[PDB]
Length: 272
Ligand SMILES: C[C@H](CCC(=O)O)[C@H]1CC[C@H]2[C@@H]3[C@H](O)C[C@@H]4C[C@H](O)CC[C@]4(C)[C@H]3C[C@H](O)[C@]12C
Ligand SMILES: Nc1ncnc2c1ncn2[C@@H]1O[C@H](COP(=O)(O)O)[C@@H](OP(=O)(O)O)[C@H]1O
Image 1 (tube, rainbow, N blue to C red):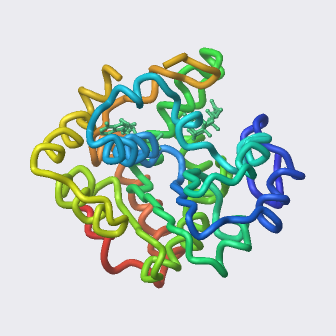
Image 2 (cartoon, protein in one colour):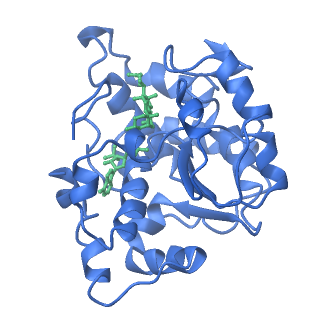
């Protein structure tokens, strides 16, 4: 289904809902949003955000689900519950910039946009989208590669979703993060988001938020609902694409990228 020329999953979304979210859904200055592209460490960051809030106690995140923890605006009829006004409102989304609520661009509510190596995103998506895809209807590696190179993937081309969203990286209320800088520069990134959010830490609580976000701890984690509960934590490693991209595929990816996103490749593109 192409909703406003955008590819979505076949359920949990509608045109009336996604159109209503872009033009008339209203964000308060006190509402926070976690916007990401799929297979980029979405659940990781979400859990880090909640674990700072609880001062590192993981009991809350064990008895909850990411959607039922940070509801997703465009997800089904969730926006109806979200219209209830409760001071601070924590939400999440996966939308590219052109379809994000137009109202947000005139208000200064806080947004965290997470990014990851598209090749690692490609590899992470390939595994997950083929984990439990009716057995042998599972897509081969080449089909998936050329499908990612074109825009044929959920929530659009990774380039347009990113280019549109990262055109605001130097804006006041925009915080851009990388999955890579969370793997390499882990504790000093949490100190940096705490500076953008005014939430402060004590030298005991820091060693607690940081313990329970580790892959292994998070790997051992309430109700398993409709989505895959166990095939989410696959590797958690950075640069697994080198185990998947042939050299001819890495050249075809480097030429598409070096042509598509021309203006942004300076900092944050330091993953290597
Ligand atoms: C169902 C679909 C995958 C279909 C497939 O097997 O290709 C997946 C891919 C991305 C998923 C979403 C994203 O992972 C973000 C959210 C994560 C939450 O844990 C559930 C809701 C949430 C909004 C997910 C709903 C649903 O499970 C989605 C939309
Ligand atoms: N606690 C954690 N620490 C490190 N990586 C994590 C993590 N939780 C999830 N991830 C990784 O984040 C990716 C999932 O992205 P998303 O959250 O957007 O669906 C997966 O990558 P891999 O498939 O490379 O293992 C998963 O392993």
